[PDB]
Amino acid sequence: NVGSNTY
Amino acid sequence: NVGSNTY
Amino acid sequence: NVGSNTY
Amino acid sequence: NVGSNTY
Amino acid sequence: NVGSNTY
Amino acid sequence: NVGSNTY
């Protein structure tokens, strides 16, 4: 993955 | 958040 | 959120 | 995945 | 997936 | 957050 962020 | 994961 | 995951 | 974010 | 975000 | 992991 590239940049599957969780906030 | 609780357990908002990215796979 | 609770358990809003991305697959 | 690319950028399936969770907020 | 690309960018199936969850808010 | 509690246990928002990235895989």
Image: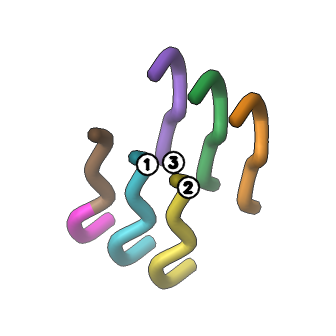
Chain colours: A purple, B cyan, C yellow, D green, E orange, F brown
Rendered view: A3 above or below C7? above
Residue D6 placed where, x, y %? 60, 53
Question: Measuring 44% from the left and 65% from the top, which residue is drawn there?
Answer: B4
Rendered view: E2 above or below F1? above
Q: Secondary structure at mark 1?
A: loop
Dominant secondary structure (helix, strand or loop) of the stretch shown in magenta: loop
Q: Which residues are magenta?
A: F1-3
Is C3 one of the magenta-colored residues? no
Residue located beneath label 2 in the image: C6
Rendered view: C7 above or below F6? below
Q: Secondary structure at mark 3?
A: loop
Quarter holding the N terminus of chain D is: top right
> What kind of residue is marked 3?
Tyr
Marks 3/2: CA–CA distance:
12 Å
* Badge 1: residue crowd in 10 Å (few <14, some 14–19, many ≥20): many
Disc sitting over residue B6 in the figure: 1
Marks 2/1: CA–CA distance:
5 Å
Which residue ends up furthest to the left in the rendered image?
Answer: F3
> What kind of residue is marked 1?
Thr
Residue located beneath label 3 in the image: A7
Depth check, mark 3 against mark 1: the one in front is 1
Residue F6 placed where, x, y %? 31, 41
Marks 3/1: CA–CA distance:
11 Å
Residue C4 placed where, x, y %? 56, 72
> What kind of residue is marked 2?
Thr
State whether discs 3 and 2 lie on one chain: no
Q: Secondary structure at mark 2?
A: loop
